[PDB]
Length: 218
Length: 218
Ligand code: HEM
Ligand code: HEM
Image 1 (cartoon, chains in turn purple, red):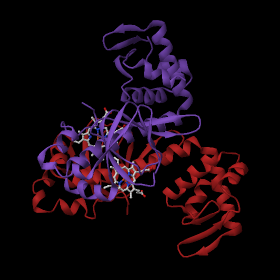
Image 2: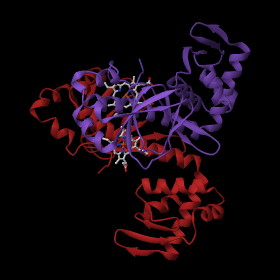
Image 3: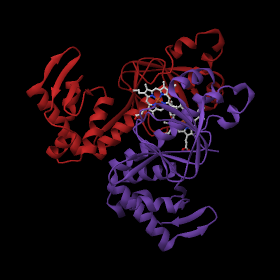
Image 4: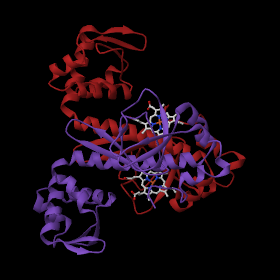
């Protein structure tokens, strides 16, 4: 149950119905091994593709860092006409078609725009997090370090993850880290939206993805 | 006008058609005065709305500055469950419904998701430009001031713009501005994406919006 979805049925199931038979015809199949770069930004051949199996990372690449924009799973649509790089996170099979062909089927077969909405919403979600993370780069680093440090020092193992009884509210965390209550508030909300953590009570957080948070502390 | 569109017809027009009977009455109307804040990030009520008339700015707000993500115009869909502020740029009338009602609408009436794709694409395009702008803040400013100077020195008026001769290729410009070749190209392509210019080759640019470019030199 990927949270950006507007429908409960996977697009691959829909495409393999007989009401959608003939749309499949216009797609070709390509395989990619783990870590293979599928596409560099704005490729010469404008393609719309569908992930058939595996996981694909859509990302902005710079010299010293990369920002993940989205992770495409089975049934997710994307294209080659963005400023993003596209990499296979695991052994991957895609189905692809020329853009001129997809123009027709997106207006005719409703299930496609529904998935695009889900994928573009996810990309925008991660983009806003990235922008917040750049505006508050230093505060974010300090907060993530504070939390990972607390997790290792006093974190408690629970079935959902690591419970952090910080004994500090957001105001007090901001004081500890030399930022504002408002900034820590934005950043914690962002960590929640990333599925990194949940709020247990005023002074307690549940760290559900420590390993991921360890990437923001570097 | 936006090139993100997958249709030529306005959602407000489609909402008047027979096939869409009953949909309109699922929305209520609210008027907003010029400069009024419609919604703060993630308001108590989770709503989907359509701009009936006026123009609405979607933006990120920090204590120092704001980043505009999109201008929504008549016929555009947005929601109240994002981390952005939403402000009326002029006297505005919106049509709003609870998200739980919109769930049924978006699945059965295809025009809504097509408009969402256009809107989300425009927000994402603006978002990626913002990200690049933050990562390369210094280099961006120095490039903009170079291009404004080059316009003053070499600029020849042509229909729809100003032809610039830089006298330098991308590597040489990079050396001059104390940056990498890769950063110059990325920022030049972003200026293209913003409608500021076209790249004829490494040495020649067509400037379509000098005024907007002077905003990056400030
Ligand atoms: C019907 C087929 C499609 C058409 C005709 C189309 C057309 C376009 C056009 C003309 C642009 C540039 C608009 C501008 O100048 O602002 C664009 C950008 C973009 N499109 Fe598509 N597109 C299609 C399918 C898709 C799909 C399947 C996706 C992925 C879900 C997608 C995602 C994007 C994104 C993220 C951008 C902005 C890229 C950037 O700023 O680097 N599009 N599209
Ligand atoms: C019935 C229709 C809708 C449903 C079921 C829905 C559902 C959701 C859910 C569950 C999330 C949070 C995803 C997560 O947990 O990561 C979300 C986020 C988001 N949605 Fe929607 N939504 C709908 C309509 C819309 C509309 C109309 C728009 C605007 C065109 C939109 C744009 C966004 C954006 C930009 C986010 C990310 C917000 C942020 O990160 O600040 N959604 N949606």
